[PDB]
Image (tube, grey):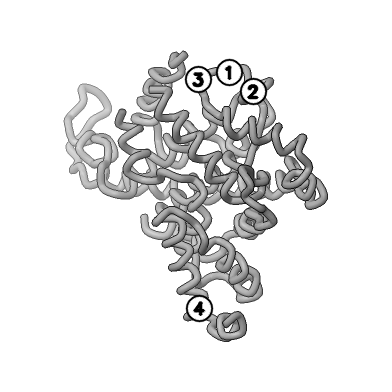
Amino acid sequence: LGAIRQGMKRFQFLLNCCEPGTIPDASILAAALDLEAPVVARAALFLECARFVHRCNRGNWPEWMKGHHVNITKKGLSRGRSPIVGNKRNQKLQWNAAKLFYQWGDAIGVRLNELCHGESESPANLLGLIYDEETKRRLRKEDEEEDFLDDSTVNPSKCGCPFALKMAACQLLLEITTFLRETNAGAEENYHRNMSWLHVMILLCNQQSFICTHVDYCHPHCYLHHSRSCARLVRAIKLLYSGMLKYIRLQVMSLSPAPLSLLIKAAPILTEEMYGDIQPAAWELLLSMDEHMAGAAAAMFLLCAVKVPEAVSDML
């Protein structure tokens, strides 16, 4: 059952020697949803990429990404040179990254803008989702039996794409923003302030809807159904197995607060019409249960209130 697991560890050494900002491709990062691959392998790739992004972010660098492996005199084509050039090589590696991680996240991101019509459950379909009992009990059984130890119920041809996969893409982009803002000299500062694909994260927050009644059920656009979805997937990833588990237990614990912290990390670049759309979302998510979720909703609402206090004044 866990024969993927060690293979991922094998994949871990395939991200231990290759150059950052070269592997993988933008297009195979974009179009990897309509194949025979479930949500769990996509999320595993997302968390592995995020793990190596945190390796390039916090300070836990690998041995070859610190400049110690070019000084020793080889027995061919070799001459005495200081390893400072190897430090420049590692400055090259993240200069391959800080561009291409932007471009790969572009190529995923506009694909997800096209995936807004991909799994597009209509508002009429949503009003049938929340109240009509048939697809109610259908997707409630699909959200409740959601665990990744049996490959027969949760994903039929290993092709399903719920909104929890979109939150997993959101937390991968979240770690991309932990890299890009902090860690060929023209667009090095032009690749953080202007991102051409961030309107659909707020759109997914508008698809984090609030027409629910919470009588033993939430509709698959309600963020409590998203909370139960990400809770079921975190329970799945803690049933399938430890250092990658260490990373998961050190970072995320719930995928529903991902666009919240995304909006904290990308506050000042937005024009304020989108702010006038995000203060209603600030009203809806302040009923949340987690300290991370409701607390980051409080800090987002705090920042949009110290930005725009008159809409706050009108809703008081």
Q: Which residue is mark 3?
A: 149
Quadrant location of residue 3? Answer: top left
Type of the residue with mark 3: Leu
Residue drawn at x 61%, y 57% as measured from the top left: 205
Q: Nearer the viewer, mark 2 or mark 4?
A: 4
Circle 1 residues within 10 Å: few <14, some 14–19, many ≥20? few
Circle 2 residues within 10 Å: few <14, some 14–19, many ≥20? some
Type of the residue with mark 1: Asp
Q: Which residue is mark 2?
A: 158
Measured from the top left, where is residue 289 in percent x and y? 46, 54
Look at the numbered disc 4 and give the secondary structure of its residue. Answer: helix
Is residue 81 positioned above or below 147 on the image?
A: below
Work out whether mark 2 precedes mark 4 in sequence or the reverse, and give the earlier one.
2
State the residue in front, 205 or 190: 205
Residue drawn at x 56%, y 47% as measured from the top left: 105
Between marks 2 and 1, how big is the CA–CA gap?
Answer: 8 Å
Between marks 3 and 2, how big is the CA–CA gap?
Answer: 13 Å
Q: Which residue is mark 4?
A: 305
State the residue in front, 291 or 200: 291
Q: Which residue is mark 1?
A: 151
Pointers 2 and 1 in contact (CB under 8 A)? yes
Type of the residue with mark 2: Lys
Measured from the top left, where is residue 71 in percent x and y? 18, 36
Between marks 4 and 3, how big is the CA–CA gap?
Answer: 45 Å
Is residue 190 positioned above or below 56 on the image?
A: below
